[PDB]
Image (cartoon, coloured by chain):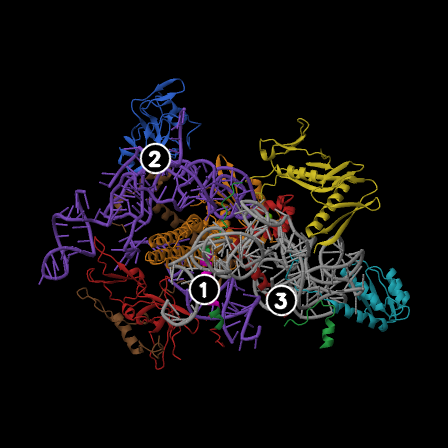
Chain colours: A red, B yellow, C orange, D cyan, E green, F brown, G blue, I purple
Amino acid sequence: PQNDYIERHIKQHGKRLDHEERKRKREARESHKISERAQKLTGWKGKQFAKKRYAEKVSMRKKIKAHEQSKVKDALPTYLLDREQKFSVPLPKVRGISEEEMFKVIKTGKSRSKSWKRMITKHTFVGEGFTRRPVKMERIIRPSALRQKKANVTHPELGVTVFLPILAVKKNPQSPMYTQLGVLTKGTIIEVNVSELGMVTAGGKVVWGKYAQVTNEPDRDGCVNAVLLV
Amino acid sequence: MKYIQTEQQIEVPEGVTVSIKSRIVKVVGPRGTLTKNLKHIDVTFTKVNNQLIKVAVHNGGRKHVAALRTVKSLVDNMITGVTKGYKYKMRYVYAHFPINVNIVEKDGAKFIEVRNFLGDKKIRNVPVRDGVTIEFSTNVKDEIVLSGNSVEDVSQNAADLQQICRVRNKDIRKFLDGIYVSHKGFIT
Amino acid sequence: MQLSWKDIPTVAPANDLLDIVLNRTQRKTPTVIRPGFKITRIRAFYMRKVKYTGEGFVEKFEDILKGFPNINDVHPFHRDLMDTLYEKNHYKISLAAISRAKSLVEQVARDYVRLLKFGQSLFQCKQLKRAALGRMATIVKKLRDPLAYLEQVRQHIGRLPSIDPNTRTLLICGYPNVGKSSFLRCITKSDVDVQPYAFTTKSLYVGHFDYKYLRFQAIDTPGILDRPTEEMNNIEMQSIYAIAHLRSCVLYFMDLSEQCGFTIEAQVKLFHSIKPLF
Amino acid sequence: MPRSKRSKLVTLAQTDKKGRENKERIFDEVREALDTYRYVWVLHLDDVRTPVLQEIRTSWAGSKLIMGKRKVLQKALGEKREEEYKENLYQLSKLCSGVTGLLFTDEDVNTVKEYFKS
Amino acid sequence: MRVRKRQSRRTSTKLKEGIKKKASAHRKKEKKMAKKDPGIPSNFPYKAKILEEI
Amino acid sequence: VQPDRRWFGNTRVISQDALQHFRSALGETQKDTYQVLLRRNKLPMSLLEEKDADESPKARILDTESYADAFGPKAQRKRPRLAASNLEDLVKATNEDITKYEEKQVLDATLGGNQEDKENGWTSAAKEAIFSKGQSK
Amino acid sequence: SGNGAQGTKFRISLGLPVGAIMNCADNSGARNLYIIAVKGSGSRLNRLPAASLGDMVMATVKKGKPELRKKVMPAIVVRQAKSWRRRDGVFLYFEDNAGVIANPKGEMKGSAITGPVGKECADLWPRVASNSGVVV
RNA sequence: AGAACUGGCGAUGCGGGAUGAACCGAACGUAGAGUUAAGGUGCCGGAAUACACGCUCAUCAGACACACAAAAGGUGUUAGUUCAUCUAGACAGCCGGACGGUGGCCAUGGAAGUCGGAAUCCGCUAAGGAGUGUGUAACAACUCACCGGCCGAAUGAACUA
RNA sequence: GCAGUCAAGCGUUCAGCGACAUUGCUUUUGAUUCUUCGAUGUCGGCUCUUCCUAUCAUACCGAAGCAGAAUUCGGUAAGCGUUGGAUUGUUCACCCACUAAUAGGGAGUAGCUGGGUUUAGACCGUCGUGAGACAGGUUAGUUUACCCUACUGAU
Ligand SMILES: [Mg+2]
């Protein structure tokens, strides 16, 4: 131990007498083994084998193309080189969300026959001073687990995307009563803290906030994605 | 495309004769005789000049042509074994525990006995197949020579002899003890 | 722990680890659920799947973290050896990255379980479970290089020598090929190359012997040159720090023959230069 | 072969087959040397170390040694009298059997033969 | 030796109707999405005659 | 959704003078326990934070040398980086470090009582569930 | 048999189920041992693990020195009090069941053992026999 | 999903698709003879184990809807399309060369083509790439791209069905 | 998930679609995690039979720095096993004791069941001017067979 003992043993004693023949025969048989596996594997193992074969073939083709290319043979400053980088909304006419969905009837009392309550089962922004009211007064319920604070906004320019706090919701289509509720409901326009991106308009009036539109459905995702409206 | 007919040529040396039945092939020569039942192959034989035999398959497919080729190869191997014979040399290597090899006899089976392999107390007996003779080499320390007329029998015996000494559960990168086929050649 | 940290659990690369975890989650847990089942059943099934995946990833990361020797505050000699061999900065950075990935996986699993507890449809729960699995897969994929580096360093550390500094040990010093390996082989039973080429031993070699019923261990080292330590290889630094940290009594070997073409004057100059360590 | 066929061992080597272009070039060179030099010799060197071949080539800078495929050299020298490049050149081409081998030089025949003997 | 279960090949006409409806929908979807020569073959012994006629 | 110049409109633009005033106020203002906050007056706090510091966290060493370069089959890191410039400095920094490590080990061993479990092989009994309250979900 | 025990052990009556209390038979200061688990016990539905003479068990000190409280340590039963068939052809039992606390290697903590020590336990545990002044 | 047109079922028997509200056939009095639809002609089951060309060996094919799993992968098979080399000896098999400037420049304990970074320049050829891979601390040695010598004739590469 | 690069390919007639890879996303020094935020609906257990492998262990093997011990993954493998317990100021889990192991799932079971649907009782808070119910909470409150089949035995 305490060293490359296997290497020293090989250099002093060598491999097995049939080791070379065994390795050569296994290498020769590898083609038949691959062919048999391509036809015998089942139970989703065939899917993985086919995917790996596809990846290997693509990699080999790309390597061959690169080798052939080798055999054939914007104006950044010195301190920035060798470094990494109509008024229509991007998503008009979003799918309409029914009023029956997103409002789960919640039943209360020993005899659950006076529900009178509604729960919003979609992500919503509830401001900074939310402070739930008494139980007897609250009708619409938005669980805290569904309350989002920071939204992922992608900059159309520079291809850079940053995680920024949500400021407010301005225009949610489909009965903007939901806008008042603050539901995201992909297709909504929300204010975002653009201060991080350092956008400055003419006149020295640095912009720390701007509009943005959510591009992903938060119902089926654990994150909020939006496209910055430059 | 189901070729109309494909044939191959088998060369029979003057020193041996090969009588063939419907599909049973018998080879006779100085060293001995061999037989093989090829009734499952469905091929035809035909003499031309008493020294060459042509095996042909009419309306045979690619697989049938391959079977014809392997039949020709088997016939050639049998002829070579009958004429020259085959000689297999096997060497056993040990690091600490010497390997004791002896040809014991019980009821005429003539098992090959290997003892003290890697210090194991178990006695390994490898039966000797028909038509193959095993003799310990002389002037080549730690070597055993297997000879016979049939390639299949000698090869299977050598494979079994080397496999019976399998190193189980130990790192093959360190334990080099075992039995290996050092060289394959003809008796002549 | 100390003394031959050989029992570190092997760690597979990022791709292999992710594949193993996903296969285990798919196999051990049930995979059959139907839309006709109550929404509670589907929610429980998907939450259980996500929790199982998170638990598997957490267990793997915890095992990897525990296995390693925790280079900090182990021992000056062992700590310095690890720093010289595995680039202690990079080793600590990789292990901290693994620990951070573990916490990220825990947070992702908890958040996704909380979100999925409010699931309202089979498709929504399936999408949430897929999102959690994809987040875990991306976190694992981000760990590609550190896992590969840690596998190699784990192999090396398992194959490293295990000397006890507190014990009475010998140490051989001098120019390469002066006879350090030969002396170690002769004095005690050990497997060390005794070839005459420049650097026969590329690392430390240990050999035990008994004198007057007391256990002793001899240590052989590649050796050092007349360099002023401003520029030096890790091989020479290993010997330098072994001399510095170890209480061992050091023996300075010399060869007056034409071999070891650093003349007697060079040997004496090296001895004088290393005198502070002596 | 629809399937179950041999697979070529593809390797990313830098050299590529010269093709028929090299053969045509050697053919033209042989036909030019047949008239550019006063004497022609057929050298049967089955195998030789490349340094030895270069030493032989540089032994006389005032001469040219042509080698390559035997068939190409034979065709350049002519296979029949009906198309031989030079009179009786078919006879010389008929004599090549080994790994030839075609030396063109204006040096004295006796000197060349003595050098080859020594 | 301990062969496992085999998938039944029975038609299960409920599946017949389901597949018929699915195919009818798919054909309509494909139709809606729709709105939104090799020359002389080789190996022919008399391919030259085509060029002569041209 | 109807197109408009808003949404691509400017809403919350701030001026430099206001930013400077708020930055000064952050360090000037102090809180009083007898007074409680009612409104935070939504502000770009990001542009006002990042006060002066003198730490300069450790540089990204991985960028200069990757994991493979530090160690592996290639292992181009043939020499230690910034190692002690002299043998005397190495001895001075190692002899005292050994004593410090011994003192730290003694201090840690003063507590261990896991040593009894390690030696005698016994283990502490399971913590009673009653002592885990009130910490339920 | 398990670690520490030497040789094979023949089955005897199991008179010490989990949760049983047996008087301490060593001078370590413990008074009685509360058995929480039995080493080498079988796995079966609804079957409570049970110990016997010479078996190694994990038990907590219900009474005795405060230092020994709240911690579970291995113990070896020296008395059973339940009749068991000896191969010699006699059924015997002790006045009261008792055990001695020991380490996983079977080493004795107390320097002496009080009261009779079962023959099976003494034979199966060399350290117990060496620390036993009375056997049977 | 919202509409317009067009049939059936409801109120509908009968033969077929094993079994059926929508599928095919089809004009419902009681009878005799004959010819047919759709479906079938190895038995249950009335009718050719009929004739002719091919396609498939499946360690749970096939007789399964035409639609989701479905993008592809098989040194499993049959037939085709497009490009290449070829008696100026086609592919594959055996033996020889695989040079010299040269151990090319940076670091180096060791780095000679094959641990790492920029080059990757030129002479002689039939050919030699500052090197395709195995291995030595270091070369050495083995081997490949190509070429050369022996037999000889079709062979190779990508796609379609 | 969204926002981008490349194209093995498809192709308004070969501008558009597009496989495998790939960048931004959600404190680099194992340091902490003292967040653990609404499931309006139950789950969890006593006896007991069978079945699936997507195999925890036993059986046979390959690949792993597999020197040993020991450990990881993978191939076949359901023949046999997969346990004794604390916790309801909750128990959609959990800890520690052994054992080779304490793997995941279906048939569920008016056979028994504790939480839950709970009915005229009763006690504290909210609403309402009231009858009363609720955001709560606490508490006291049919049931087979001798008929047929199914199974175990017997003429
Ligand atoms: Mg040496």
Q: Chain of mark 2?
A: G
From mark 1 to mark 3, how far is it between C-alphas?
48 Å
Residue E51 image offset from top left, x and y in percent: 72, 75
Q: Which mark is residue E25?
A: 1
Q: Secondary structure at mark 1?
A: helix
| Residue D20 marker | none
Q: Which mark is residue G46?
A: 2
Q: Nearer the viewer, mark 2 or mark 3?
A: 2
**Dot 3, crowdedness within 10 Å: few (<14), some or many (≥20)?**
some
The crowding category of the residue bearing disc 1, from other C-alpha atoms within 10 Å (few below 14, some 14 to 19, many at least 20), is few
Q: Position of residue A11 (x, y in %)?
A: 62, 46
Question: Dot 3 lies on which element?
Answer: helix
Same-chain status of marks 1 and 3: no
Q: Position of residue I40 (x, y in %)?
A: 27, 55
Q: Chain of mark 3?
A: A
User: How far across and how far down the image is residue D41, in percent?
Assistant: 86, 65
Segment tinted magenta in the rendering: E16-30
Q: Name the kind of residue labelled 3 in the image.
A: Glu
Magenta-colored stretch includes residue E28: yes
